[PDB]
Length: 368
Ligand SMILES: CCn1c(CO)nn(-c2cc3c(cc2F)C(=O)[C@@H](c2ccccc2C)CN3C(C)C)c1=O
Ligand SMILES: Cc1cc2nc3c(=O)[nH]c(=O)nc-3n(C[C@H](O)[C@H](O)[C@H](O)COP(=O)(O)O)c2cc1C
Ligand SMILES: CCCCCCCCCCCC[N+](C)(C)[O-]
Ligand SMILES: O=C(O)c1cc(=O)[nH]c(=O)[nH]1
Ligand SMILES: [Cl-]
Ligand SMILES: [Cl-]
Image (cartoon, rainbow, N blue to C red; front, side, top):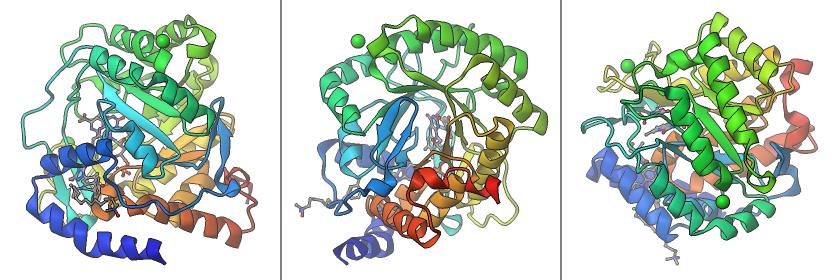
């Protein structure tokens, strides 16, 4: 097809050539700019009814989203929908602006189809992002009604003395502009942050977040999800599941990047500090989805993320318990045509495996 034409040219020629000329962070910035301007190949893929999912109080035209980190500051939302994503997540956004870690802080591992990053929550801050989303608020209301929801991922400032207050501020400022919020407690690149996944600290934090969310007017009241690491102990996972059910958290995003370094990585930069993403994370993420689905009795929507680059990858996460999936790292290797690729392959596999649509496949492995 013309679809598989672009896919091949991008993956085999354009992307490796451009990536060889650019610093990884320059590549990131350039990608956000081009996306923001809508300077994109044609997304010829027409979303099928088979791909629609109803979860988190919304219709999703397709189950493939852009993960947090690509558009940290909400600059490229419309362009990301033009790429064919069924939903967009922006952030992480911190309350105050902050620079993040010194450069270089992003590393390519092409032999592993992986990235390592240590951005450290570089953010324009809540006020900037609020004004950016306000400028297109009604455009987004129509997008959401048309099955293209918006998520906002909230972080905390490096120097904050009260983490829960940083998240509360995010709920109050960006909650009214979001379909869902994410309490990101799983960056590997902010000191002490992942300790907020622990039981006592998590219950107190999430209680505060949910109280702030519940105080928003109805049409401005988002779902609240918790994004977790792939590096949790069994105890940590059980505790999260317990808290989520007790408080009525609306969903989970599973997973962030890993601080592990799986045996077999080949890239020269494998021992850089930071979170590892892409292919080496894939199965660690899938198995975290599987465990969290079981621990929550299939009653808590999961957005599955980590190492998705194909329809098989997406379907493995769906069958393990994800209602929706995200990707980021694949885009850095394949470019924009990867979105249509994943969707096309996923549709084909659903038909081959006897599923009437995505919904029927959610958690299917648990019923074998
Ligand atoms: C992890 C940081 N990081 C890295 C380095 O690790 N790369 N990277 C991306 C670069 C990208 C893209 C997507 C990316 F995620 C595109 O989709 C590319 C693109 C092609 C044609 C038209 C329109 C677009 C937007 C352009 N490129 C580069 C060649 C500039 C990115 O965020
Ligand atoms: C450069 C980079 C920056 C990221 N920044 C964030 C972030 O600000 N917030 C967050 O929740 N996740 C962040 N992530 C994690 C992704 O959202 C995702 O959970 C992870 O990369 C696994 O998906 P992937 O293998 O498809 O990239 C970032 C990932 C990368 C590669
Ligand atoms: C930073 C990426 C550089 C490559 C950009 C490729 C943009 C191609 C999309 C332009 C729109 C398509 N058109 C009308 C020319 O066929
Ligand atoms: O800003 C970052 O360093 C970052 C945040 C996050 O949640 N995950 C990640 O891999 N990087
Ligand atoms: Cl508002
Ligand atoms: Cl590390």
